[PDB]
Length: 72
Image 1 (cartoon, helix red, strand yellow):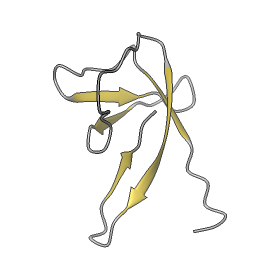
Image 2 (tube, helix red, strand yellow; image 1 turned 45 degrees about the horizontal axis):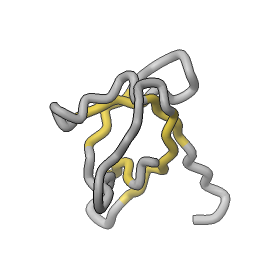
Image 3 (cartoon, helix red, strand yellow; image 1 turned 135 degrees about the horizontal axis):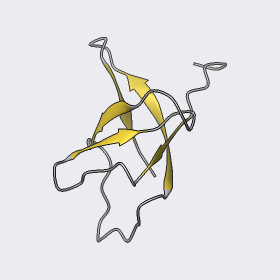
Image 4 (cartoon, rainbow, N blue to C red; image 1 turned 135 degrees about the vertical axis):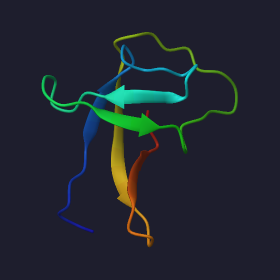
C-alpha cells in the first residue's frame, strides 16, 4: 500500500499496437520489459507519435500475478 512507489516510464517508439504487444523502457537505458493492453483503451481514438513517454504502475491481483495497466 502506502510507501510502495511503482512509477514506470515507457516510449511509443517501441510500441506495437498492430501486434497488440509493446514494450517499456524503464530507466532510459537498460533492460526492457513486455507489456500487454488490458486497460489501455479510450472511447474514441488516440493521436500519439513515436517517442511519447507514458506513465503506469504494476498491479498485483489476488491470484498472485502482476501486470501494468492504465498506461497514459
